Each structure stands twice: as C-alpha cells, then as structure tokens.
Length: 241
Length: 248
Image (cartoon, rainbow over all chains, first blue to last red; front, side):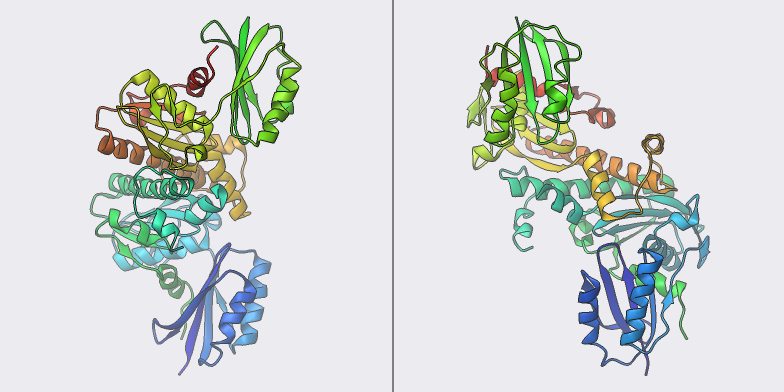
C-alpha cells in the first residue's frame, strides 16, 4: 500500500513521521538541520511513501527548498498547509489571520475538532505557546514565551534531570537555573489554566503537546497529552485520498 | 563629604551618591564603563570623599572600573567580597563563592532589615529569587530570565518576532489572549513572569511560613507587585547590603 510522510518544520527543528493508514506511525524523528533530516529520511526510503503533507513556519523560499529535497527522496507531490480564516469549524482569532504561526493554528484547530468544547492548548517546545478556543470554535487568541531550551542556552540531559529532582532552592548555579526556569514554566502553565477558567469555564478541555509537556503535566491532572497534535491538524488542513 | 556607591552587574552599572547615612542625592544606570565615567560628569558637583562597590565582573574588569574612579575622586575605594556570613546571615551555596555578590548583598540586607524569614526577588534583566530562614540562614535560590532576556531569546529564535516599543507598551494594557504577535509575546512573557512570582510566594509559605516578609527589587518590580500587596519594594536593596559589607 501507500504511506504518508508528514512534517512539522519549526524554527529550529523539523519533526517528521511516516504513517500507515489513517494515522498509525511506523517511523519518525527530530532533525536539528536539513542535512540531519535528509540523513534520517534516507534510511526510510525503503518505506512505500507515496504521499506527503507538511506545515512550516519558515520562509516561503526555505520551505520550497525543503519540498524540493523531499520530492527528490520520495515519489510524491508534497502538500503544504497554509493560513486560513477558518478550518474545520474553527475561527482564526488574529487581527490578521496570516500573522498566526501555522503550527499553533493547526494544533488549536485539531484540539477543538477533537473536543468540540472550549479548550486550552499549550505547546511546551523550544518556544512555549498557549491558545484558547471558545466552545463554539472561536479562537480567542494566545500567548508566546520562551521554553526550557531558550531559557537555558541564555543563562548557561540525565544530569539536568538530576538538578530537577527537587524544586527547592538551589545551592549551586546549575540547580538555581534549572529549577528557576522550570518553576517559571510551571508558573506560566498555572496562569494559563486560571485564564482559561475565567474565559472558558472550569470544565474546559486541556491539551498539552511539545517535548516538555511531561515537565508540567502533573499540574493539570486531567490534561490530555498529545505529542502529535499538530499532525492531527495537518491532516485536516491537507486531506489525502 | 559624601559616598559614591556602585553595583557592577554583567551589563549595566547602577550607581548613586549619598549624603549622610543613606540619603541618595544622585544616581543612574550606565550601560557601559564609558556611559558611567562621563555620566558622573553631566549633573556634577557632589564632593565625594569615600567610595564602595560590589561587582560580579572579572577581577580584571573590576580594577578596570576602579581605575577611572581612583582618579576622578580622592578616595580609597572599598570592594565587597564573598563571604560565608555577613551581618548575621549565612551564605547558602555549597561553594559560597559561586553566589552572585549582588544577590548576596541584597538578601543579607533583607534579613538584616526584617530579622524574620524572607523571600527576596530581583526583577531585572535576569530574575533571581532567594529565601532566608528566620535564623538568618540562606536556603539558596533561583535564577531565570527577566522580560528583556525573554524578548531577546524569542527574537533570536525567530525573525517573525519584531515590533516597536510603542506597540510593545500598548500590548501590556491587558493580559487577555493576544490577537497579534506583540500582544501574544508581551502578555505571554509577563504572565510567565507573574507566574514565577506566584510560585516563589507558594514556595516561601511552604519553607518559611505564611508569615515571611517579601522584598522586591529590580526595575520590573512594578509589573508584579500587585500580586503581593504586602511586598516591600526596595529599588536600592543591594546598597543597604553594600554598606554592611563595606562600612564607612
């Protein structure tokens, strides 16, 4: 049969996966550079990839280049997600709908599509984003702030996890920074939940995504953790056969 | 005769001149060793006959600043140094010398003034928070980015984040969901900042008791003080500690 290669092209990373059928992932990875990406994908050209869809927050030129390299590695005609005032019953909340990062857009649309209720959508990645959508599908807007990665490379994995074994006051540089930043991130999440309760109601659905979701999930007992949220939205934005 | 006081941070150099025990009559933020020596020129007259300072810079850069000072004033400059104890306060870092000297003097000043357990947060380019038990024992602290650093990080992360100061200030008039880049970024970062402060307050109530005194310093203290009505805002906290570290 034919499989689909999906990609999320962020500012500093490219996440990809190949799915069989509707959404069963059989392979995927994270590339810190296009060369790393080509390197990883080259090992999967054995897979019957015959379709491709992706979302990108990079320049129109940078994306076309990537698309070109993709269409070289696989016999496909890549679909590229684009800005919209509406998608799957969800209304873009930006003054200028095109100003909304496409990654945030697809994820928040995916969330409302799945919940059909008001929801809080938080992406804990390199950068952190939070978006709120009313029960009627209207996007209220959102927020942006740095993630653990950006906060780190500014003031400075198994060893860092050790510094994070406690959130009590640090007695050494490494501890102060790691615990400081995580408490700042955890603080942000609580501010988002409070804001959502106020504008969406206490029973709103909560969606967490991004590689650092695990660091804050304990704060919201009922939150739904979905590493591939954006990809759910990408299927809606670029439907295939 | 007056005293010239300086706080040499990694970037800016906050200074002031005081008459008597601590009455400030002049001061300012010098973003560079140059925007200082000359900055002590503009509004000038003040007859300083003593000087003390704390610095978190290389022992090189230190005398590099002390240099153009030992010449501008007939004073034998006093420099604050690390310590395991000061004015009844115990340094809480495993290696007492790794603790930022500015943080150190500010938290010591706080306990010196309260004589109770305290939470001390400095809302500057970078944000720091330290806790001190009622017996004067520093439990340690936290370090994280402040507003300017968070903006800087995001700016560097993506070219899609760029706007005017005017648009930036406009954005902070509300904390509701942003509907434009400046609104999402400015409100996001401020909520993260306000969020960090609430976590610190919770951590303090836990380890120090709900009775602990709260001290806020740094230029961005105003952005978060409403969260702690009882908070004591002290822009010059570090200088209270400098006098304890270098008495005159």
